[PDB]
Image: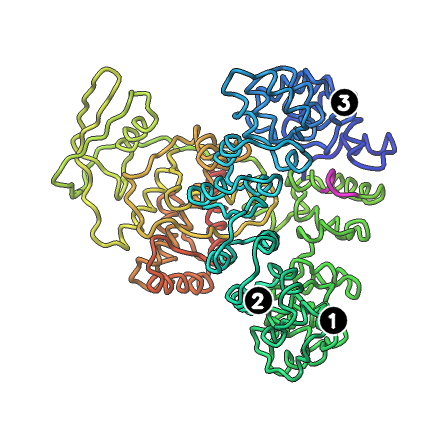
Amino acid sequence: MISVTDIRRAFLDNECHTITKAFGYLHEDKAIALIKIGFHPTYLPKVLYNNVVEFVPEKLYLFKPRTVAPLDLISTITKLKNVDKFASHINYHKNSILITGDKSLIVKCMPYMIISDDDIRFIREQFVGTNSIEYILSFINKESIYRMSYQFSENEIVTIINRDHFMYEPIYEHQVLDSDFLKTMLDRYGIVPINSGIIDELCPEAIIEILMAVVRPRDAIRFLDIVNKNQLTEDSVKNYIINDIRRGKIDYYIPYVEDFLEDRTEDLGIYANIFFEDAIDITKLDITKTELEHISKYMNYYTTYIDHIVNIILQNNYIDILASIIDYVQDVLTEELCIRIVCESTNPVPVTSLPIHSTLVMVMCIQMKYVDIVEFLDEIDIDTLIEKGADPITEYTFTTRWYNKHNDLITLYIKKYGFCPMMMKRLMFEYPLTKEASDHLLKTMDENRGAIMFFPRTICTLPYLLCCNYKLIQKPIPFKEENRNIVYKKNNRVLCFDSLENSAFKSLIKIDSIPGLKTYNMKDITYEKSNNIICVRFIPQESIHNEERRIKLQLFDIARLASYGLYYIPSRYLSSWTPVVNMIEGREYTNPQKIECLVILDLFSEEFIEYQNLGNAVSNKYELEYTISNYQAAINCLMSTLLIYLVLGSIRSISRTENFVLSILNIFYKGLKINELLSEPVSGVCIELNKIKDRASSGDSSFIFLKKNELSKTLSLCEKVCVETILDNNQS
């Protein structure tokens, strides 16, 4: 459990109403320490302003913009790369920032400043004679344009659209543009010319093509309005719009239909009533499932016929359609139907939209992993929820008032997250707790110190172990004298490096010193130098012919290298998958959307990085918001490699998937020198894996596509292997 002694002392001895207020009564030294690591309220009292400016300036945004001094603000954001959090400060002090005349400063601040016609006059004054005017203005935001009278020149508009393509949207509805300029922007940037500057009469084909290309409904409306002022609308255009309405594209055309298609309501059929109140009696029409899907978003126009529609839905078992109109059928929903919806619908419905909150409905929502199970507490007590397997501590719950209505939910929040600084920060500071709720929270955490509240399941979960802030101990490399009968390639290989300090060079040499590797072996290493450059000549191990054996033996080597402090970032397979970050922040995580390879390459192709530099390499490779430790980066690399070797390895495997998962994960243990065998149930994992295996033959693509939440059991097994990796490391 996170310690709360000091902040609870502050909360009680000053009779605060919120933990935010109590934070301000901490000793300035403790407050500043907490502020540095991000454990702070959303704002700070003025007494701390000088300490923040001196000791942690990047956190000045925690003061009201009026409280911050323009010099302090400008000194801070000059140093920072990301100033998103200073947006309201930057806007409030825009005049101070303009007066500086600093090109780099102004350009960094433009996306957050609401720029006025006067401000534009100041920029053209301070920068006349330089390339900078069209450069500075190219960083303007859509908010400035909406409130602006100024009109961009064409050069400005190009510079702006080169910097951010979709800035054409505010520009195109801000000002009248030359019609040849609109054509040039279409031929060259593919921008659809939706602007009042359209002057030439367009052929029926041209109108149909522009409609087929627009995406936002407001652009279709605008286009048609402009065009109708230039020319009459053809029967060819009218026909396409009716057929587009039949394809579900409705919002695009509501003004148009109401003004020009009044005499085509029989062609519009069931859709006509969206445009003309009760225009067609739909009971006399043959209604298709597709037509009901399209009008589901438009049911407020079919309330005259709501019974007929509901009846078609129930008679044809259109449960997804029933779910999509659930707000209109509250009176019809029996417990039986409520259950059907929960089990059969593609996407969940809100528990508040189910009028029946029986235990039976609740266990179906638990089975379907509904995120809003807490809403059954109007009928069912928290103990029955927990006994029946509910987890009400979700993101959904945080958007409700339930934490103030029920101190048992705050206790459950602590049991799930009391060790997790980011999640406790969120409840302590970013949730509108009551005095009594705030008191219960700090009391419960203070009287349950240590690990007792997380025993015996949570203390052995990966997120819990990531927040103990352990270390992975590296083992020293044993003496090597290679006696094995290794088959080497009949050709040598040369790798060159800019210097001998090169970390990749240093790890290649270290890996050569490591005994007992199965795939990463090298013969007859010679050196050649040219000033700083160092080249390594060597004869690589011949590749293992059996692909399944090769993949198993590569994971052994990965485990053995990790035990000695050498890791690799699997970014060629999972370019953005950092589940460790989710875990230490208390956020749920799921599988990546794809594996960017089909073939597991040999380990010679990867760059192995020292543990001591791993936190920095991982955070840079994945462009993380903040730098994670070497420990947490090591866990991410293992989690990534395990997922890749299980999924990709399965695909290329010829043995029974149950024996593959069990033997390659035991192979991983052996590389770690863990003497106990892995013995986990893999039946549920193998069903997930075999599904993906079957798409990989049918797909025929350059990547392996993974469906959302398809690998939950495989991920819990990757987690369990990492947990055992950490616990065994901590015994040594």
Q: Earlier in the sequence, mark 1 or mark 2?
A: 2
> Residue at position x 42%, y 56% from top?
705
- Residue 347 image position (x, y, % from top left): 60, 64
Q: Earlier in the sequence, mark 3 or mark 1?
A: 3
Figure check: 236 above or below 371: below
Q: Earlier in the sequence, mark 3 or mark 2?
A: 3
Which range of residues does the magenta coloring cover? 427-432
Rounded to the nearest whole Å, what is the CA distance between mark 3 and mark 1?
53 Å
- Residue 126 image position (x, y, % from top left): 60, 15
Quadrant assignment, res 335: bottom right
Figure check: 334 above or below 492: below
Which residue is identified by label 1?
358
Residue 67 image label: 3
Label 3 neighbour load within 10 Å: few <14, some 14-19, many 20+? some
Which residue is identified by label 2?
245
> Residue at position x 60%, y 68% from top?
294
Q: Is residue 682 magenta?
A: no
Badge 1 marks a residue whose secondary structure is: loop
Query: Which residue sits furthest right?
Result: 15
Badge 2 marks a residue whose secondary structure is: helix
Label 2 neighbour load within 10 Å: few <14, some 14-19, many 20+? some
Total tally of numbered discs in the picture:
3
